[PDB]
Image (cartoon, rainbow, N blue to C red; front, side):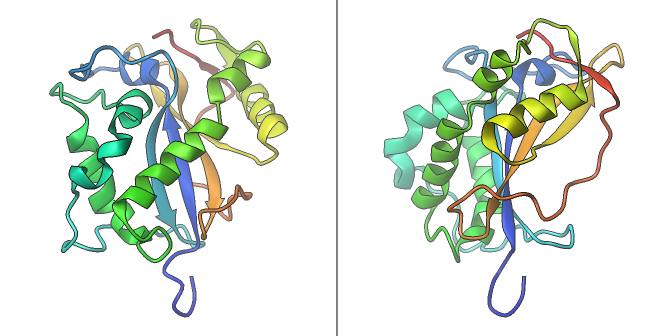
Length: 208
């Protein structure tokens, strides 16, 4: 990012809950119930074109849920936390704003605009539907990494980045999908750079 531009673009990252709840650690359900079996938002992260990113940028603007009271039921459905201990979600959302949303205050000027941007992005990138449409289902099969990639790329027109983790038995599985968004927050772009990590050739899609 040069000049007075704070950062170069965003990753918009969604997570599959079945690969959060099959690992060596316990996941917990939030207090509104087991979530729907769908990708959820992990976060919308400002990032730069050298692989670095801004973080914790404004400690004088702590998260304030009364500013996003109109979004909360959408946030309950589409951005649930599965970390322990069971909670309403506010811990997770507080954490995303403080670490990451505070660094996008140049473009997305207040909390409400930040959270509403991530919910509008989820609503146009339906990953499940896209995958299902290519016959790729969370049914515990292993699928070739190239097919999942090409299915998303054919549907949205930009290449996603797939991050894997490993389940309790050590098997490499579909964890999170990152799509990139321009520095304005207005449109999908090809990522300028991709994060590190390894998936290997064939990966599970766990049931949830």
